[PDB]
Structures are given as structure tokens and as C-alpha cells.
Amino acid sequence: KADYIWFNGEMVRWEDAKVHVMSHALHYGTSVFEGIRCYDSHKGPVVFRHREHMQRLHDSAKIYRFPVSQSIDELMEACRDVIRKNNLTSAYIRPLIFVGDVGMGVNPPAGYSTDVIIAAFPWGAYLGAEALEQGIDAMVSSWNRAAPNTIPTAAKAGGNYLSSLLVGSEARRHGYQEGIALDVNGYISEGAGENLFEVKDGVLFTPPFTSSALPGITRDAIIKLAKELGIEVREQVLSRESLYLADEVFMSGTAAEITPVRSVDGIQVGEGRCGPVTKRIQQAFFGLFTGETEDKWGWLDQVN
Amino acid sequence: KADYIWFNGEMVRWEDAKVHVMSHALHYGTSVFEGIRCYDSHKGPVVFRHREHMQRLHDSAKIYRFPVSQSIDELMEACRDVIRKNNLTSAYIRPLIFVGDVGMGVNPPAGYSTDVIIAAFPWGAYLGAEALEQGIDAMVSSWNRAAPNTIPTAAKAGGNYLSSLLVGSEARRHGYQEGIALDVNGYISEGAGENLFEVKDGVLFTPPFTSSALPGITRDAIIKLAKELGIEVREQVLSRESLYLADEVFMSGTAAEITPVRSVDGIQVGEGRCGPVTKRIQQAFFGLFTGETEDKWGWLDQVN
Amino acid sequence: KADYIWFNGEMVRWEDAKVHVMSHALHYGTSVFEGIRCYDSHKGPVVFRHREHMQRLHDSAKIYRFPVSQSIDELMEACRDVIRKNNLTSAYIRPLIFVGDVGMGVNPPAGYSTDVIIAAFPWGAYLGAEALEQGIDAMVSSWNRAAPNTIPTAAKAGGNYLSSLLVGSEARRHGYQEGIALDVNGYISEGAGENLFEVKDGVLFTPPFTSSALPGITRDAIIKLAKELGIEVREQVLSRESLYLADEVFMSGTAAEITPVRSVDGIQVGEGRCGPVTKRIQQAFFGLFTGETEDKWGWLDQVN
Amino acid sequence: KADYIWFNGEMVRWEDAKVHVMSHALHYGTSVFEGIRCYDSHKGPVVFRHREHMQRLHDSAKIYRFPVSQSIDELMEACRDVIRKNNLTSAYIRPLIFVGDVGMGVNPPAGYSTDVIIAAFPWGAYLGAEALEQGIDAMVSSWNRAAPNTIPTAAKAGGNYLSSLLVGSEARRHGYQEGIALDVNGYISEGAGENLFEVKDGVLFTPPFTSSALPGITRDAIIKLAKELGIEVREQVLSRESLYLADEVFMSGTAAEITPVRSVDGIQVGEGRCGPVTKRIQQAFFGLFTGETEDKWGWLDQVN
Amino acid sequence: KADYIWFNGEMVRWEDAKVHVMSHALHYGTSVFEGIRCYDSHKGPVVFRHREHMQRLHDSAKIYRFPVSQSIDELMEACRDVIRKNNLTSAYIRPLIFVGDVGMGVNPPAGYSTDVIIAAFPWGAYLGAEALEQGIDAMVSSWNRAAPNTIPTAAKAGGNYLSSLLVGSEARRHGYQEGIALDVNGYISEGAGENLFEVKDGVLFTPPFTSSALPGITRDAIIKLAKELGIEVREQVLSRESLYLADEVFMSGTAAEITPVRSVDGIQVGEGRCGPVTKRIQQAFFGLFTGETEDKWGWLDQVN
Amino acid sequence: KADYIWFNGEMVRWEDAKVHVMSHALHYGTSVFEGIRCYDSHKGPVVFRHREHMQRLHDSAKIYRFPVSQSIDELMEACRDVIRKNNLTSAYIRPLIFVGDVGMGVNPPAGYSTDVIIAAFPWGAYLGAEALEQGIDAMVSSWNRAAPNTIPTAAKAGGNYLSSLLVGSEARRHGYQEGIALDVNGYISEGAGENLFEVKDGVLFTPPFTSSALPGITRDAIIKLAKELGIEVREQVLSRESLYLADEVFMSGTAAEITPVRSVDGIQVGEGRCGPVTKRIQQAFFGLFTGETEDKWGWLDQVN
Ligand SMILES: *Cc1c(COP(=O)(O)O)cnc(C)c1O
Ligand SMILES: *Cc1c(COP(=O)(O)O)cnc(C)c1O
Ligand SMILES: *Cc1c(COP(=O)(O)O)cnc(C)c1O
Ligand SMILES: *Cc1c(COP(=O)(O)O)cnc(C)c1O
Ligand SMILES: *Cc1c(COP(=O)(O)O)cnc(C)c1O
Ligand SMILES: *Cc1c(COP(=O)(O)O)cnc(C)c1O
Ligand SMILES: O=C(O)CCCC(=O)O
Ligand SMILES: O=C(O)CCCC(=O)O
Ligand SMILES: O=C(O)CCCC(=O)O
Ligand SMILES: O=C(O)CCCC(=O)O
Ligand SMILES: O=C(O)CCCC(=O)O
Ligand SMILES: O=C(O)CCCC(=O)O
């Protein structure tokens, strides 16, 4: 929570940011959202890969044909404006584009407009306060990720998350920190809300998007970072059991950043701590906010 | 719009039924809903298969482990109460149970509670003012229905409607009234928001739930009415091309009631009009609200 | 061979029934056909389930939207005319609707018409001289039947037969009389060019159309004969290994009639000879052309 | 049309190139063919990747075990002879190997030979007059490409085209220029009769053959031209929604050459016009027949 | 454990029943086995559905072409002989047919013989001492059952059990009594070593064998018993979530007999105790050994 | 047969290496094994990729959670010790870890231990005395390889060989030397007990592990040797028909080493003999044991 929320171009106090219970999205999962982090850095408060996230917000909307009135630059300014208007230097930002109060049929009435919200607020490590340093214990879920050509997994939409709820809630109920879902083919897809990476013999592996995995922006950053670090990367389908044979394993996400996975289904991964390659990647990722890692791609948007 | 809406145990005026923009369901499709019709009949206003719908509402929630505080009878009284107060004699009732303002993680905090809304309002034939009489032109969608064990299609959840949007809007954009979706195996599943029935040589056919089709209450009713009429019924998987060979075809649902399908993909069905068996079923169905069809099951819940 | 072939309404000498090499179907498999048998019965030469076959010819053409100018009755009269013109009392008839000389694009030009042929000629036991009496040895093919929603297996089309060729030729190359193909799910579909039945504990079994099996007219007749004989019938998916556990197994088809399968993949079926249930259906079937079996369905169309 | 057609070695007047209506391929889709273009270049009339096409003709026939008596060199010489005999300097050539008048069983009799035809004639832009310059509007089909191990999609066979007909005619019926088919896994396969390419972030993408896509010779040429142009190429599975996120999309084929796709399912691709990368490949491709692009692969076969 | 084990026709003392470590089955899973119970009854010690089990032993062997020298009657006598020779009146019998010391290639040398063992010994309720009366808590496994046409699930072979080990061990590790596996389609298959039954609205449901479920003999007994009890039975595919909506649920097996399942994945089934319909079936099953249930099928083989 | 066998830490004479008939693995396929060859080389007897195999042996056990007491080096010394004692200079070593006499439930009792055996003995070319030189005739099986997430194909377990038996014995019964299996998707997986390689236009191809193929150690070696030879290698999914178009094809394995495949399904590959690239690879492979090929990886473990 924070003091204000950007709501359709106007800064509204948090408590007054409300919508009608008959809003389309509450009944039909009709919304697309983003996860963005603003970090403290040597350059001051910076939003990580800001433009890439707003571009994806638009892409998700385009896929479902949800009309978006704000341009990417407007959404970005709006985002920076809510970060300052709330006096935050570090935070998690949640943009949300949803079909609002427009009538009950699943097909929105012609000419409708979508509602847009953007809330920023501090948010701890997604998988725990000990996650980033100690790693977590994962569980392969009994629920599979959405099949191709059903609900586009390339789009980050609200409705998709019933699946992430089933996969993630199951792991927790069974005492694990996160759940790893397989696609309808029996191959590794990703975690409930984070992409999956494996390390074997010094090479980094990760499932392609066609494994029903969302095109993670953190995932993309890690691949390019790894290439810079001289680490070979292979985007390929991964068997379920490969999780038990990898030297290292970890998850990526805007919220979960880079979280080592010390075990899967009770089976220890490597030494049971953060692996050497994971450490290198992790250090290179954060060194970006210390300036130790050169921002060669222009991934740090300054809030001002 | 109506005048009041049942919101968490109390009837609030329509304009005040609002929830926070950070309500879980707006971001994660975490809601389950129902569709119910109140018919003005020879016995005055009656809710059709009222209890069955509230039970299903409970089952959907149970599947996702969404905590529900109200019992079926409680919900039933609330529904009935909503119709009276708004002074409706015929209407569409939309009960809705969703995870509200509980924080931003997809996994809700332990001990949370859901918000429950029940709105009622008049709503015309779902597929057109001519639909029920002249029948509609349907299109087979290029989008498939959710695969087994990904999202439970036996549950009527809000999140899953992203799929119905893709299926239904496509047919509509191409000039049809509704889209028919195949499951991931290539067999007929159902319409975007209606179950699919076919008639050939006097026998009634419809896919089983395992064809990724919702276990519709209108569908179950039709199967029963058909049997009472001596019409043989076969619940079995159906081929996509079977839509072109069927003597008759129609859709079913609370909103769409019993809508004949006069053409599929531009291929006329039968004589391009409502078929004889669809006719009997339909007359039998609507005969319930005139007394011509004896309510031998107890499907009419008097509003009072 | 025979003397005349009905061609677009005309009785053409067999040697003059030719088409340009640039005819569409020779390049794109764009044709639909039927197999029909005229038997020399107690009622004289009669065409078996004549209307049913011509109706299917139309259905197959309809699925592909091939324009057909002859009505089912026109087709039937032409068929009888062909038989008499060649003075045949028993024969195999091959009606064939195909896209002809209309230009090289796969999509035919608007307003085009199809060419129609009906050739009648004597044709013996499809699966061999001993087949009907002693049964054949079948092999499960390494090639699978077409998947649902690719090339509609419910339509009897020319292009379909590339599959039948692969399945059948393989079995024959390995020394068997016919090949049994499995669908893409690994379940029994049917023989390369005939439906497959199994007999277990006095109950008759056969796969539904959704197992990528063509809705055989002979298959349909068997099912009806079986029920008149007091034999329970079950149309359900069948496992590949069920072929090794069945008491009896046989194939059906217009050309193949009812052929007993004494062995599958070298494993013996029952006594390795025609089974008792098979025997009954067979006698019942052929008894239709001697009068021993009453034509309660009106399956014998008098040629005259 | 043209004056002569090479037929089993002889130069036959177009009007005399006929086959019996009882020819095997007219009933069983038993034929394999090729699309080849002769261009009027700076070197005179040349057949593009002539040997490659005839080799594929043989491969396709080999897969089905169709006996072929002409060698690749005999076929090529016949093709050049056909072109010259019709005094053509630019044309589309259609070689066709088919099972002819050999009896009605699907399995041809032992010792049979195939009939071979090579017809040459002028043929314009496969996808329209503006297609090459302005791009077309594509639609994702509701029909899927043949599954692996059913009908080998690597073989260019006549029977295959029933699928291409369904896919293409649907798009055309809905007002689009071409249809894009997905495989049975829900991933992009290709266009009804052309391979599909995507351009994203300056990188060229196209599905592998295992996505049920025919190994296009034009596709292969593009990949080679791309690498000479310094364009990175990635043959990988592509999601259906990737079509909406790609910077550019285009189709390839002998008939279709290189046709830009400006929109998919009504959604605009990039600027809605030919993309920059597409532009380069296109110029590079056509520059082969003007000399601007060096034939480093020996793709221009002199007709003489 | 007991005093003697029937080993290739000779009663050997338990401890001396050994085989060479190079026995085929230890390296290739090449064995087929059965589970049979002998009960105390009013008729004295009786083996339940004795002939049916030995017939299946033979069927399993036939499927893998393992030569079996003993006839069914010999195996039965041998079985009764080990029950008496060990002085048991109630017990679990384990027949085992395995490829022995014949060399290391997976394909056994031509002319080989299989080894056969039959051990009887008391064995408590498979799923616990409180299982049959209180019911158990089940868990849907993250491991799926074998796909059709890979390893025939209709055959009860040793090699198959690696799967039952993965499914069952997982449920236990997570604190459950048994695991329920879904097939590769996402539908209910069965428990790790027991068939699955569901009860909804007084009707009994169970997956067909094509759901990759073994043709349980206990399962078969229950179906016939239910029919006798007037209970409608439907053999059909069941969705994963149906487990959460059934009134009752239970497992069947020779070892587990009839075990109520009070919960699945933490979700209570019905009232959480043995359900009414399950009780009826259970009582009817055991009444067979008290003589209260008439043995109308001849399921009780007397040991003597 | 040899003279001694390493059995649980001590070398016992061949005739005494026996386990109880009630050993878990005999009834449940619960064992994991390896295949290793000892070559007499320019450096005397050397075990090929000794450590890699013992590691894999450990990984397979870890996948099934089979407790292993010995370390890799321990196992390695035991292997080496087995070769010396038996006085072999070249041989096939079969390590075997299995669940022994621990009770009759599929789930072993907590705290159990596995039995470990390591046998060595001379073994000729796996597919014939002419195999490696003349190549073999292969057949595509009608049985498919285990699907992902059913049985982990990344583990070399005994139970899974029921599948290799079905695949391999079929080809053998039809007169071929080995069978090639497709996965459940219809793509090439591998041979019954060998990985499958294809050569086309100088490039080496082989399916990835995700094609249900074991991650062979000979396969990995070949990929490395090929690269050292400048041969491009592509690990990708391969179509079934690609077997007929490849210039060269061969199998790989510890037992089969590098066996050329001269024909598939009766269709000759290349010139019907070992192909040029297979030749180079092979010469490179066997060159390791003469010193001609520099062991640049450390694949030869001296027996001493
Ligand atoms: C948001 C999300 C991720 C992480 O992607 P980032 O762009 O790196 O935040 C991963 N998986 C799913 C399903 C997601 O919704
Ligand atoms: C609500 C719904 C139906 C219709 O079910 P009824 O219970 O008859 O209203 C059909 N299909 C889907 C996908 C639905 O959501
Ligand atoms: C024609 C055909 C049959 C047989 O059907 P009938 O109507 O009985 O002749 C069976 N299978 C296939 C694939 C066929 O084409
Ligand atoms: C012929 C064909 C193509 C195009 O291949 P080219 O060799 O480039 O002509 C593409 N797809 C299909 C289905 C085809 O038959
Ligand atoms: C043995 C077994 C059963 C139970 O079958 P019964 O004949 O009733 O003993 C169920 N599932 C599997 C996988 C089995 O092996
Ligand atoms: C053992 C085996 C191989 C060969 O692997 P290598 O490590 O090279 O010996 C190939 N396929 C299967 C199924 C195997 O079991
Ligand atoms: O990582 C993110 O930014 C979004 C996923 C986390 C969640 O909202 O559950
Ligand atoms: O709101 C919709 O679009 C679906 C309504 C479904 C029903 O209640 O029948
Ligand atoms: O022509 C064939 O090869 C099969 C025809 C099938 C039939 O007519 O029954
Ligand atoms: O004939 C067609 O319709 C397509 C031919 C494809 C080609 O030759 O490129
Ligand atoms: O029920 C049976 O008879 C066999 C399965 C139990 C087991 O051996 O694990
Ligand atoms: O024993 C077999 O039949 C397989 C041997 C596999 C290998 O070690 O290469």
C-alpha cells in the first residue's frame, strides 16, 4: 500500500481507487497487467527495463484487442509520476489495463474503452526474505500450464492466473515455496509466476516460449547478461527429470528477481545452496544498480 | 442496471456496489460466477433450476478453494430477495464470488474471505432478437478450448472467459452470431458460452464434459426433457465435420436458452431453419413456464 | 472392365471416358467417391444400401464444398442405368465426383462445376479368395490414421487414400493380408480400407468415428444386424492390445464385405479361424440376398 | 494453356494429354508433383533450383514407393524440352508423377509403372497482382495441418492438398488472401500452400519441418540468401500469437515467391506494408534474375 | 513370508527360492504377475476369482509373447497346493512368470523358457489397518500413467510398476496413503495400484481401460455386483476435478479390496467417511465369504 | 558367463551370484543398469567413458530415489577389479542396482538398501557379426516410446525395457536387425537400444532427449568427435519420413557401438552401404583405441 494510485490520468488517493462490482474484468478475467520494479541505484531511483514492460502491456492488450488510449511514453511518465507522487525510491509497480463497467456480455460493446491503473508500493522478495540468498525448495505441480492456442501464454493477462493459483497454491499446501508447472506435453514450462533456468556443465538452459512459458523480461535480461559473462545459453525444451540432474536451478521474475532453487520434489540440487553460475548471474544483475555492471543496454530508466 | 444489488449479506443500491481496484480478481481472474434466469410464468416469477446453479457456484469455488461463508439456501434467499426488491418478474441473475482486496500476490493470505455479489436485471435473448426463432449462423473458431488439467473447465470461473472472448469475438468479427470451439484433440467442445447439441436421424447428441465443455444446467435439463419426450440421447465425442452432416444443431445455456443453429461455416443445416426435434425440445422447455410441460423435477423456484 | 461408364449424364463407351491430365483431382486429391455393390439376389440384381451411399457421396462433397448438380435420386437412377447398360447382375460400382480441368490453383475458380463418373464392373473378394471363409492375418501398422480436424475422416475423399495406401502396402510387404491402423492417440482406428470389429465375451465392439474411422455403411449394417440377432453392441475406443485378447476380430467394408481376422501381428485370434459371432453376422449379412434374412430396413434397391 | 505437354517421354499436343477416368490418382490421391518457375533473366530463360525440385519429386515418389523410370537428369532435360517446345521464356512448370489406369484396388498391382507429365505455362502472382508489392491479409485457419506420421508432410503429394484446400478456401471465404494453418500442437505450421516467415528484432524466424511444414525450396533459398545478407536465422517452433507480435511476416513458395503479410486476423503487422527485412530478401531474391545478386549456389539452370 | 514357494512345479522352502542375478527380469522388467486372495468363508478357504487371475497371467504373457508351459488348470492346482502346503486358510497369492537366466540381450534367445513362481502368505489391508473402514486421503500425482501403445497397460507386468512406484511414493512422501494418476490426456486413470470409482447422484462411475487403467478383476466384480444391487454403472472418462465433486470415491484392488477415499488433495469427499453407496458395495463384496451374498457367478474356488 | 561377479562389495564366483525370487526388481522392474565396454587398445585394456557411465548409473538411481551406498570411484574400482580378476582384455560390463528382497509392496519399506552387481563378459557386435561393416536393415516399429512424464526416459532403468522388447522383437520377427521407435508425437525417438543419427548434405542430425530418447554416452561422444572433425551437428526433432531422405543413417550405443543403417522399411539408404560421413565418425571412434584419434577428453580409463 501507498498514498496514491494513478487512475485514468489522475492521481487518486489509494482508498478512493474503486470500481463497480459489475466491471467486466471481475466477471471475465478481461485484463492485462505488468510487474515492474524501481530500484535505488548510483544513478538514483531507476525503473528496470521500463519501456520493455509498457511495450508488453500494449502487446498483451493488442492480442485480446483491448483498446488502449495511453501511448507507451504516457504510461511511462504516468508510472514515474506515481513513484514520485508517493515518495518512493525503490518499489514494485503494478500497471493494470482492464475492461470496466460496460455491460455483462463477455463480448464488450462496440466502441468501449478500457480503464487503466498504476500502483507503486514497496514489496519484499516474492519467494521469501531468505530466498535470494539461500534458495528455495520447489515442487513440480500436478496441474499443467495452458495448452498452445487456448489462452495465449505470451500475453500477461489476469484471467491466466487461475492457473498460476492452482500450481502455486499446491506447492505451498505441500510445504514448498513455489510450484513448477509442466506443459501439456510433459516438459518443463515454468514456475507459477517465474521463468525457470537450469545449469549443467556450465551451460545455462531455459525453455522456449512455445513450452507455454511467458516471455519473461527478467528472463531476457539474464540471457543477455549470461552472454556478456561468457556463459553459453541454450533455449530448448527440458524434460521433467532434468530438474533432478541439473548442477544448478533458479527462477527469474520481476517480483522474484533471481531466486536459487536448492531442491525440487525433495531432491537436492547440487550442494543445496546458491550455485556458482547462479551467483555470477545474480551478482551481475544487481551490480547494475551499483554501477559495477555496465548498463550496456540502457535498462535503467531514471525516475527523477 | 437495476436498483439494488445483494452485496455481502446486505442489499445496497446499485451505484454503491464497488470494490477496490486492487481487488484480487481484477488482477488474477480469481472469481466464479453463475447465470440464472427468472421467468414470469403461469405461476408468476420463477427462478429456473435455482438450487442447481447455487450448488454449482459452490462447486466452482470449492475447486479453487475460495472460502464461501454463505450457504446455498442463504444464497437462494438472497437471489430471490434481489428479484423482489428490484420488482422484476423476469430477469437474468448474476451471482459472483471473488477474491477481493487482499494484497497483490496471486496466492491470497491465509484466512482471507471472498466477497459475494448477486445482481439481477432484464436481459434479452443472448444471440439476437431473432435467434430463438430463426436460429443463428455459427462459425468454428480458430482458438481451442482449455485443455484438461490446465484450467478446470468443470468450474464456471471468470478467468476462463478470456477463452470465450477469443472464440466468440472471432465469429462476431467475421459476421457470425457465435463461435463453436473444438477441444485440443480436434473434437467439438462447445460454443463460446453455450453447450452444443446435434440431431441426426431423430437422435440427440452432445459432447461429454471431458470434451472441455462446461456441465451446463440447461444442457442437463434438455437431456432430461428429451428423454421424457422419448428422444434417444447420446453423450459422446463429436467430430468437427459432424456439424455439416447433422440434421439439426442448436446451442444451450442460461443466457442463450435454446438457440437453433441454421448454418455452420456458411453451410446450411437441414432446411436452414429450426429443425423438428429442436422445435419439440424448445416447445417442451418453454412449456414449463406455461404449465403445458409438467415440472416433473422441481426446476421452478417461486420468487414469492 | 465393362462397356460403358455414366459420365456427366451420358453413357460413354469405357474407352472414351477420359479426362485431361491437368484435371484438378489428379494434382490435388480433390475428389470424393463411393464403393457400392450390386448383388445377384433372390429379388434379382439389387444395389445394397444404395441411397445411403449416394447420400454419403453428397455429404463428402458437401464437406469440401464441391458443387454437385445431380440429386441423390438422379445419382441412383444413373447407377441403375449403368448396371443395366453393361448387362451386369452382380458388380462393384464406383461413383466419383471430382474437380476436373479448371486451371492449376488449388482453390478452384468461382462458378466451377464438378465432373461425375459412375463405373460398374465385376470385382471379387477384396481380401482374397479364402478371406471370407478362412479369415486373414492382419498387422498393426507403423503409420497412423489422420488426426481430427486435419483431413475429415468422415468424408470419403480421394486424397484420404494416401494414408490407406501406406497402411495397407506395409502389411502386404510384410506378408500379411491387411493392415490395422491406430489413430494419433494410439487407439485402434480401423483397417486401411475397412472398419474393425472385435468380439469379447459374446459382446460386439467397434471404435466410434472419433477414433478417425470412416462411418462405414457396412459397419452400420452389421451393428443393426447384430442387434436383431440379440447381440449386444458397444461403440467405444479400443486399446491396441485388445486385439490380442479378443475372442474374435473381423473387418467390414463394401469391397471386403465381412472378412474374419484369424491373427494379428502373428498372434492367433481364438481358434485361428472364423469365430462363432462373426459367423452369425456373416450368414445374417449374406442371407440378405437369398431371402433367409428379412430386409427390414429396405437395404435392397432393385436395379431392375 | 500451352501447345505441348511432355507425357511419358513424348511431346503431346496439350489437347491430347488425357488419362482414363479410372486412373488411380483420380480416386486415391496417389500422385506427387512439383511447382517450378522458369524466369526470363539476364542469362536468358532459366529454371530456378531445377535439380532441387526434380530431386524432391523423386523423394516424394520414393516415400510412397511409386516406381519412377526417369532419372533426375532425364526429368530436367524433359522439363527444358517442354519450355522450348512451347517457346516460353518465363513460365510455371508442373511435373506430375501419378498412378494411372491400373485397376481399382488402393494397392497398385505388382510390376506397375507410373505415368509422368510435365506441363509448362505462364502463371502470374499466386496471391494477387498487388501481393508482392503491397502484402496481403492473412487469417489463421480453423483447420489444422496433417499430424506427424499420418500423411508425410515432407512429401509433396496430391492427396495432401485436400488440407491445403480447406485451409485456403476458408480464408478466401472470409475475405482474406490466404490462410495460415497451425499444426496439431497448436503452433504455426505454414500457409495453405506456402511457408511462413516472421521477422522480430532484425532476426528471421520460420518453423522447422517437424511443425508439419513442407521443406520449401523457396524457403530454403530465403534462409541461404538471408545469411549472405548478414541476417540471423532461427528455425524454431512459433506460437500462434507470435504472428501479432512480429515486426514483419511473409510467405514463400514457388508460385507465391515472396509475399509480404501486412495483417493477420485483422491485426496490423508493423506498418501494414512490406517490412524492411522482407524488402531486402525480396530484392535479393529477384535480383537473381537480373544479375544484381550473384548465383553463388548455382540456382539458375539454363533452359537454352 | 511363509514356509514354501512353488517354483517350476516343485515346492521349495522359502529361503531356497533364489535366482541368478543375471536373470533377464532383473535387468529388463521382463515378467508378468498376478495378485490373488484366498479368503476364509462358510465354504472354507476360497480363492477369489481364481481362474480369472490365471487367465490374465496368461494374457499378460501372451501380449509380450513370453512362453508359458503351465496351463491355467495346472497353475490353479499349483496355487491351491501352495496354500495348503503352507497351511493357510486366508492369504495373498503372488504368481510370477519371468524370463530367467538366458543371456543379456533384451531379446531373449529363441527357444527359451520362462520361470514361474507362486508364493502365498498373509498380507494386511494394502492401504492400512484403518483403510477399509475409515477411508483414506489421496493425492493426484504429478506423474502420469503410461501413454497408449507404449507399454500395454492391459498387461500386468513387472516393468510397468516403475510408474506405480513414482505415483505412489510421491503421495506418501507428501503425507497421503495413495496416489491417483492421470493419463497423458489429463483425465483420471487410476490409483498407483488400484482402480478408481466415483459415486455421484447414486450412479457409479469408473474410467474405461483406454484411460490407461488396468482391467481390474476386483473392478469387474464391483461393476457386476453394483448391477445386481440395482446401481447404475457408467464406464466413462472422468475429469480430474470430478474427484472434488463426487459424492463418494473409492479404490478397488485384490490387495486393497474396496477402500473408501475420504479426501483428495486435502479436499473432503462427501461427509469424510465411507459413503452410503460404497458401504453397500463393500458389504455385498464381503457377504460373499459369509454366504450372505449369493455367489451367482462362481467366484469362489475352494482350496480343500 | 565369466568367473567372478562383484556383488555388494565382494567378488563372488559366478555360480553364487543369486538373489531371492521375491526380490523387488523381479516383480516391479525396480532396477537401474548400465552398459560399458572394455577395449583392448594400444594402451592395453581400457574402459570407455567409465566415469560418465557410473555417474549416469547414479543419476538413474537418484531419479527413482533408490539408495546407493557406493560412490562413483568405489564403483569404478569395482568395475576395474571385475575385469582384471576375470582376466579379460576386452569386454562388456553390466553394472546393476536393484531393490532386492525387501517385502512385496511396490513401495519399499523405509530405510531399505539396494543390491549392486557388476558383471563383465565378452560380447560381440550387438546387431550381428557383419553389422558394423555392412550396416543393417532397420524397421520403424508399430510400438511407440514412453511419453514424457510417465516413465523418465533420461534414466536407464530395467523396467522400461519392456518397451525396447516390443520395439526390437517386432523388427526381428519381420526379418530386420533392429527397430526404430517414434515418440508419442510421431517423431523419431531412437532405436530399441541405440540412439538414431542421420546425415544429410554433410550435416549430422539426431533427436534431442526430449524426443523420449536416452541421453546416450556413445551419442554424446559421437557429437564431440564429429565437431572435432569439423562436421556440423544438429540436435533437433526429426520426422519419420526423414529416414528415407537422409543421405546416411546409423545407430549408436555401448553395445552396438556405431552401426550403419543401410535400409529403413526396405528403402535403401544412400548406396546401401556405410556412408562417407558414418565412415569418418566410425574410423574416428575406433581410432581412439589405436592412438590415431587423440583422446582429447579423457575417455579411456586404464584397467591396469
Ligand atoms: C510475469 C510472469 C513471469 C515473469 O516475467 P518478468 O517479465 O520477468 O516479470 C513469469 N511467468 C509468468 C506466468 C508471469 O505472469
Ligand atoms: C455458463 C456456460 C454455459 C451454459 O451453461 P448453463 O448452466 O446451461 O447456463 C455453457 N458454456 C460455457 C463455457 C458457460 O460458461
Ligand atoms: C470406404 C471405407 C471403409 C468402408 O466403408 P463401407 O461404407 O462399409 O464401404 C472403411 N474405411 C475407410 C478408410 C474407407 O474409405
Ligand atoms: C509446394 C508447397 C510449398 C512451397 O514450397 P516451394 O518448394 O518453395 O514451392 C509450401 N507448402 C506446401 C504445403 C506446399 O505443398
Ligand atoms: C493389479 C493392479 C490393479 C488391481 O487389479 P485387480 O485385478 O483388481 O487386482 C489396479 N491397477 C494396477 C496398475 C494394477 O497393477
Ligand atoms: C543404453 C541405451 C542406449 C545407448 O546409450 P549408450 O550410453 O551410448 O550406451 C540407447 N538407447 C537406449 C533406450 C538405451 O537403453
Ligand atoms: O513478477 C511480477 O511482477 C508479477 C507476478 C507476481 C504476482 O503478481 O503474483
Ligand atoms: O456473460 C456471458 O457472456 C456468458 C453468460 C452465460 C450464461 O449465463 O448463460
Ligand atoms: O478401392 C479400394 O481400395 C477400397 C474401396 C473400399 C470399398 O469400396 O469398400
Ligand atoms: O498449385 C497450387 O495451388 C500451389 C502450388 C505451390 C507452388 O508451386 O509454389
Ligand atoms: O493388488 C495386487 O494384487 C497387486 C498390487 C499391489 C502390489 O503388489 O504393490
Ligand atoms: O542389453 C540390451 O539389450 C541393451 C544394451 C544397451 C547397451 O549397453 O548399449
Image (spheres, coloured by chain):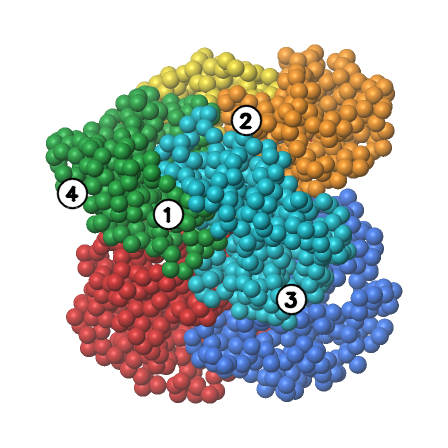
Chain colours: A green, B cyan, C blue, D red, E orange, F yellow
Q: Secondary structure at mark 4?
A: loop
Ligand 1 within 8 Å of disc 4? The answer is: no
Question: How far apart in space, not on screen, are marks 3 and 1 (Cα)?
Answer: 39 Å
Work out whether mark 4 precedes mark 1 in sequence or the reverse, and give the earlier one. Answer: 1
Question: How far apart in space, not on screen, are marks 3 and 2 (Cα)?
Answer: 48 Å
Q: Residue at x 83, y 65 (%)?
A: C296
Disc 3 target residue = B274
* Viewer-side residue, A200 vs E225: E225
Judging from the image, mark 1 belongs to the subunit labelled A
Disc 4 target residue = A298
Ligand 7 within 8 Å of disc 1? The answer is: no
> Where's residue E255, x and y in %?
67, 23
Q: Residue at x 70, y 79 (%)?
A: C73
Tag 3 near tag 2, CB within 8 Å: no
Disc 2 target residue = E266
Kindly identify the amino acid type of the residue bearing the numbered disc 1: Phe
The reply, left or right, for residue B201 in relation to residue A28 is right
Circle 4 residues within 10 Å: few <14, some 14–19, many ≥20: few
The reply, left or right, for residue E175 in relation to residue E282 is left
Question: How far apart in space, not on screen, are marks 3 and 4 (Cα)?
Answer: 63 Å
Q: Residue at x 76, y 48 (%)?
A: B296
Tag 4 near tag 2, CB within 8 Å: no
Judging from the image, mark 4 belongs to the subunit labelled A
Split into 4 quadrants, where in the image is the C terminus of chain E?
top right
Judging from the image, mark 3 belongs to the subunit labelled B
Circle 3 residues within 10 Å: few <14, some 14–19, many ≥20: many
Kindly identify the amino acid type of the residue bearing the numbered disc 2: Gly
For the residues beneath circles 4 and 1, the answer to whether they share a chain is yes
Disc 1 target residue = A98
Circle 2 residues within 10 Å: few <14, some 14–19, many ≥20: some
* Viewer-side residue, D214 vs D118: D214
